[PDB]
Amino acid sequence: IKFTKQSSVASTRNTLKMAQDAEAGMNTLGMLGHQSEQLNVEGNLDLMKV
Amino acid sequence: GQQIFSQALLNANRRGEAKTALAEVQARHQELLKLEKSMAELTQ
């Protein structure tokens, strides 16, 4: 039972850690805002239509 | 003119019937590795 609890603590440590790691979702979203502004290209395209 | 000692009997034998505490201890481990695998997939 002490061994099992030690294994559980080790795995919860790893779990929190990987959760933090995924929390990459920020670099993705921030850059998606960046490229969203870049696609807002649309301004140039409208001007070409005129 | 007498003295005695005493010996305890530990009992708590519901736990002792099994290893000791396995209700929310060994099951927690069981489902916690599952959390680990699913999180590994989520981060992947």
Image (cartoon, grey):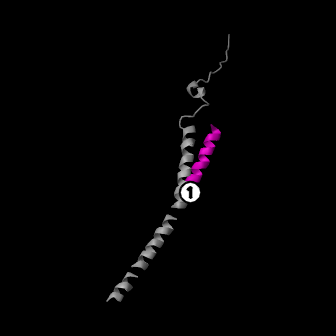
User: What is the chain identity of the residue bearing mark 1?
Assistant: A
Q: In which quarter of the image is the N terminus of chain A?
A: top right
Depth order, front residue of A23/B1:
A23
Count of picture labels: 1
> Farthest residue toward the front?
A49
Quadrant in the rendering for residue B19: top right
Secondary element at tag 1: helix
Q: Residue at point 48% right, 72% down?
A: A31
Instruction: Name the residue beneath numbered marker 1.
Output: A18
Residue B24 part of the magenta-drawn span: no
In the rendering, at what x and y percent does residue B11 appear?
59, 23
Q: Quadrant of residue A33?
A: bottom left
The reply to whether the magenta stretch includes residue A4 is: yes
Q: Where is residue A25 in the image (x, y as percent from the top left)?
A: 49, 64
Magenta stretch secondary structure, dominant: helix
- Where is B17 relative to A2, above or below? above
Q: Nearer the viewer, residue A45 or A19?
A: A45
In the picture, measured across the screen, residue B32 lies left or right of residue B2, that is left
Q: Can residue B25 be seen in this view?
A: no
Return the x and y of residue A20 as percentages of the image width and height. Answer: 54, 59
Callout 1 amino acid: Met
**Residue located 64% across and 39% down the image:** A2
User: Residue at position x 57%, y 47% from top?
Assistant: B33
Query: In the rendered image of this protein, does residue A36 appear above or below residue A25?
Result: below
Looking at the picture, tell me which residue is in the foreground, B29 or A6: B29
Residue extent of the magenta highlight: A1-18
At which x and y percent is residue B17? 59, 26
Quarter the C terminus of chain A occupies:
bottom left
**Along the horizontal axis of the image, is A50 left or right of A7?**
left
